[PDB]
Amino acid sequence: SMSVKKPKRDDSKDLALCSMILTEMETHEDAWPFLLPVNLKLVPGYKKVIKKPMDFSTIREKLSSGQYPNLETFALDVRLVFDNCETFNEDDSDIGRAGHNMRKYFEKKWTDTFK
Image (tube, rainbow, N blue to C red; front, side, top):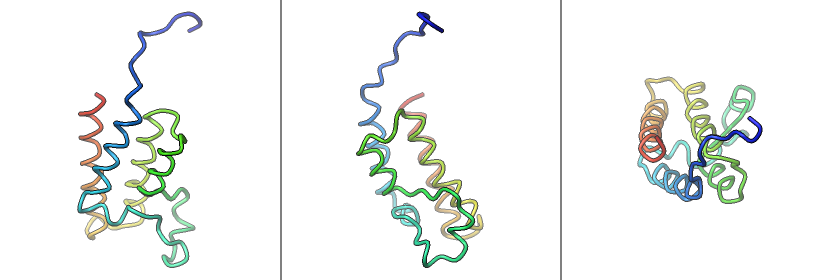
C-alpha cells in the first residue's frame, strides 16, 4: 500500500530474457504456423472468429518497440497465440499438435527463466 512495498525484484534483464525465449520459440521446428500473422483475406472464418490475432512476428515487433509494460503482458500474448490456435484447429491436426508442443516448450522456458 502507500509507503509499504515488498522488496524490489530485479527486472532489468527481463527484456533481454523475453527476447531470448522468443528467439528460441522462433527457431523451433514447429513454429511455422505461428511465425507470421494469419492471412485474414485467405483463411475463411479467421477474421470473425479470432477476435485478437497474435503471432511471433507481432510479438517480436511489440517487444522491440517497448510495447510490453512488463513480462506478464509478454506471456499473455505468447499464450494468446496458442489459445487462438486451439480455438481454430482440431487437436488431431499438424497445426493443432504444433500449438500444444509450442505451448509446452514455452511454459518450461518461462518457469525455468523466471520461477
